[PDB]
Length: 246
Image: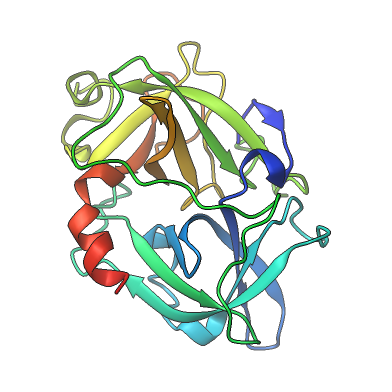
């Protein structure tokens, strides 16, 4: 997250921190995700496509920090890693950048709600906030494009939803952006998602309910003028989510 503010997991208790274990056994951060039901985390396919094997991954819930443990955190293996069969990648503009991880602990259990672990509601079909609405994004991604390290402390920021018509302008993203994607950015371009934020939540309050409107997907650099963050438009994938979570 470029700009924005530090946070703890209490302020985004559905945030899932996804890591991968290497041959060698080193564990490194991969991507963010969101808990949509006790057994299911939603994320982005591009996070996983290079390494599509479920044994490779570990999911934490209730975790506020990247490389240290948070009190009360839960650790999960990935029982099933479901990638969207219509995924594709452009130079960068991934289509259908959505993935599902069925989580279960070593003791064969799913998530147990607590002060630090909660689910996020899905939107109703094709029901998004109007353009200009302020929404929030959360992640452990870079704080500056030039950074080598990821922040040790979770971050969040606010971005405003951009209309498809605005985002499809050639000086924005042209044909790279589809109606199944959502653009969001700061009016000053001063804050944004960045590398390592992929798969994480874009959350909007829609009719008084906190809602998983988007999933961090792609962008041309970070916090650059005319170059918004791009998000998988969750309200366009409900049948896919519903079939695959059974």
